[PDB]
Length: 246
Length: 246
Ligand SMILES: CC1=Nc2c(nc(N)[nH]c2=O)NC1
Ligand SMILES: CC1=Nc2c(nc(N)[nH]c2=O)NC1
Image 1 (spheres, chains in turn cyan, green):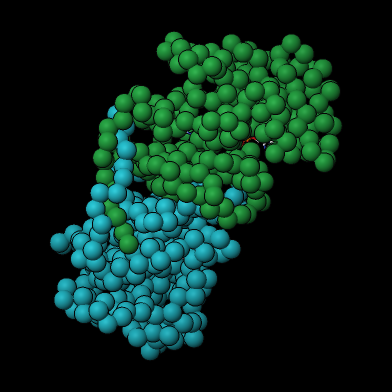
Image 2 (cartoon, each protein chain N blue to C red):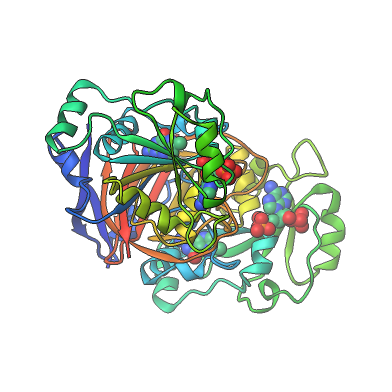
């Protein structure tokens, strides 16, 4: 019943993008996260200490493939999100696939309370979207004039964000290939609301002990079955996994 | 830099034990845990909902290989630990390796506050060890007379358990091949105190959302590097991993 996995194929920068290609059409919400063996998502507030050159390479690839990168306001404040940076060949590849040179960033906030000089607004080639509620969309739009496109993502309830509506709002703007990088509250809502199509997860070969949070937080509790699409590795013992619903 | 993993070898019940063999001599502390993709260790207080036939098989194998199974009093109370059960061929294999027919159970408690009719005491072929502090060892020994061997595992401080001493106390009794199954507080102390030699981790193909705890809890924070020894899989997309310090 059990099979040993081992390295069978060295990947070229030609086949690697193929492994992480989005579907032909339709919207697709992919998450990319890293965590330790004992399930911790941070080493001192951030993920980076666990990320080596392999994970950086995968991380930048997934950004290169995406139409839009969706992130919660907390992770934007804490990981210090600036704009999305794309190098020359990355821009070239994107153009080859019919995409803009650099993917958009979309910042999720229920409150709408964002400030004008954040790096997402300042250190950026392309103005970001702000995904918020019907209730606060107009005021938010007014405060962030010239800095960001503000989009109401409410469903039945004008005072909350409906995550399926959020996804539809991106799709309607031609941004159907979606990548989210967190943080844990937002991922938690995508999981709880069952709109996550795929999770790419880097399993870093460390144990970090009990303090760290998981890659998801919140009161949500589900049991969503995924299919293992692939597992990659490198020389340092990292596992780069891709799982797809259902 | 990246390599695709895939199934290269179907394992027989002859080679599987070889993959998880303990070292020739010296003490070795192995942990076995299961968790979801998003790092959750429980689905409603227990692990079992995530465990399929493959994980049950690995779980029973690791118990078959161990000299002693070490568990915290919390997990004993909550997962409803009875005795360790071994089937006929398992008993045979154990005898072949020079081991007793059924491995001992050792229950860790700083307080020493255990009751006489727990299933570890009642539904058991072999009396368990209770690993506690110098401070409470004598009274605990008196309360549990006839039910358990009580062992003081204090180092410098008679009011605490020193986890390296705990390990030495098992070794001194010929129980050098140690398996721990938790719970999260105990694993947290083994990690924090750096006495964990190996982690076998079943990665279950589910996301569970933000509520669940990790396989480790506590205030501990470390960054302990492990080496990936192997990754197995089955038809259902589970990954059975084995990582070794350092
Ligand atoms: C904030 C954040 N960072 C990372 C991430 N995923 C990977 N692989 N690596 C990362 O470093 N997503 C979340
Ligand atoms: C309480 C507990 N259960 C399990 C475990 N490990 C595996 N693989 N599977 C389990 O079900 N250790 C902790």
